[PDB]
Image (cartoon, grey):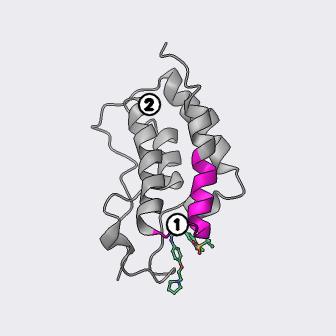
Amino acid sequence: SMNPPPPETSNPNKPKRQTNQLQYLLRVVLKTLWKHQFAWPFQQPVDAVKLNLPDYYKIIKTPMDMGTIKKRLENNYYWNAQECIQDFNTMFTNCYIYNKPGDDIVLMAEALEKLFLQKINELPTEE
Ligand SMILES: Cc1cnc(Nc2ccc(OCCN3CCCC3)cc2)nc1Nc1ccc(Cl)c(NS(=O)(=O)C(C)(C)C)c1
């Protein structure tokens, strides 16, 4: 069971903005999670062939990862902060949907999500 194409990261016809909230999502939120010791399983799409998870992309129909989020932010792909926040939440939820409680990967996601939520709590007001 093969891998799907990754999520879209480029679309010239999509309206997009560079806002102070989206800048915070890159400079604070993404950067903080990316450097974390538990980030690496989330820094690129799940390679379900290499990990031998032939059911992964049958169960996870809206895949997301921080490599995709990083590219979207670096490309100014988003219209607003909530679109990007949704991507992070999809990533975390997908982890909890696919895996067992207490699994290492879940503990890793939980550590990243705690930091995510702390940073989002201080999202600046839109300028
Ligand atoms: C983002 C993400 C979400 N869900 C999972 N689920 C998962 C991964 C592998 C699993 O193996 C099961 C045993 N195999 C299956 C057949 C036999 C062998 C089981 C479940 N993976 C993720 N990314 C990831 C990326 C790189 C790696 Cl190396 C890992 N591996 S890991 O074990 O979870 C680790 C980070 C080392 C704790 C996960």
Residue tagged by mark 2?
Answer: 81
Q: Looking at the image, is 95 positioned above or below residue 33?
A: below
| Displayed-image quarter of ligand 1 | bottom right
User: Looking at the image, can residue 36 be seen?
Assistant: yes
Amino acid at circle 2: Ala
Q: Nearer the viewer, residue 109 or 51?
A: 109
Residue at image point 51% right, 81% down: 50
Secondary structure beneath dot 2 equals helix
Residue at image point 50% right, 29% down: 22
| Spot occupied by residue 112 in the image (x, y as percentages of width and height) | 61, 50
Alpha-carbon distance for marks 1 and 2? Answer: 29 Å
Residue 42 forms part of the magenta stretch: no
Residue at image point 49% right, 70% down: 100
Q: Main secondary structure of the magenta part?
A: helix
Mark 1 packing: few (<14 Cα in 10 Å), some, or many (20+)?
A: few
Q: Looking at the image, is 126 positioned above or below residue 116?
A: above
| Spot occupied by residue 9 in the image (x, y as percentages of width and height) | 40, 49
| Spot occupied by residue 47 in the image (x, y as percentages of width and height) | 48, 73
Mark nearer the viewer, 1 or 2? 1
In the image, farthest residue toward the left: 13
Task: Tell me which segment is drawn in magenta.
Answer: 99-113
| Spot occupied by residue 88 in the image (x, y as percentages of width and height) | 47, 46
User: Looking at the image, can residue 77 be seen?
Assistant: no
Residue tagged by mark 1?
Answer: 101
Identify the mark nearer the N-term, 1 or 2.
2
Q: Is residue 14 left or right of residue 37?
A: left
Q: Looking at the image, is 10 positioned above or below residue 83?
A: below
Give the numbered dot on residue 77: none
